[PDB]
Length: 13
Length: 165
Image (cartoon, rainbow over all chains, first blue to last red; front, side, top):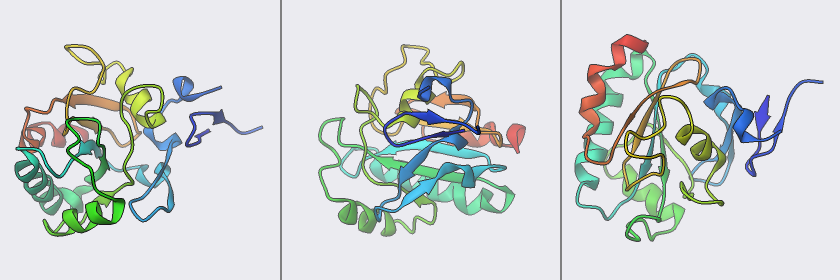
């Protein structure tokens, strides 16, 4: 999982 | 899904002081100190010199230091990122310098939003960052393990480091 500079989070699909 | 769901400092990203994006998963396996810095505080010299001391003495054991400039406290970091970079270099800083950010409020960098709500990152006296040179100790898994306030000189962290190496 990664949190971008703006604070949104995305994980493995 | 947002920063509130993050499980580790390693999920985050930040611009380094040269403007280049850094994935903080580079710190996987490394005990880290995350601190907000400023160049024009009465304790700027003690903090930078002691952070440099810690890095000199413990980098080979895995200590890393992430320094985030911020101008939110008394306007004590008014300069450009280049100026701040040069200032830090004058203390022989060899740890990692980041681009200036906010640490409180809605525009705070998400890592700082996250650290402040962690079980060991919440303040004894409330979560907001109170002044320049707050320090968070982060274990090798990216979990916050302790918070040290502006009045706690960096060498006090040395007492706790071997517990996390």
